[PDB]
Length: 129
Image (cartoon, rainbow, N blue to C red; front, top):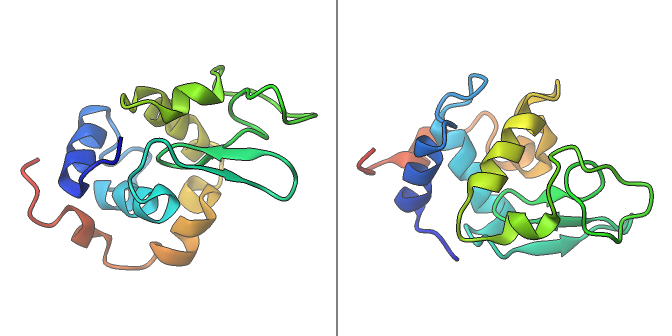
């Protein structure tokens, strides 16, 4: 499923992300924009052989199991498959663990390079929330 911008902001807010660990809602929508272009079925292969899944491009090296990343962990206790579904619950619950890991949203390289320090409120401009 490819979400609309305000449609994703609402789903995110309903799942408890707005100001989660101090990161306002625009930060989370900006990061999803650059990671997946709002497509829950996004995947991408990394040079190390691990894969990124879903709306926030969560990595199989630490966070989910895909049965093909030698030496990896499954810290969110889920199949990477769960991260591709129309229902974002699994991606949001796993994002919560990641952002709580010590580095904040710097865990998402695209957030640090493309969203951090910018006018992120813009991404929730005009939405009924």
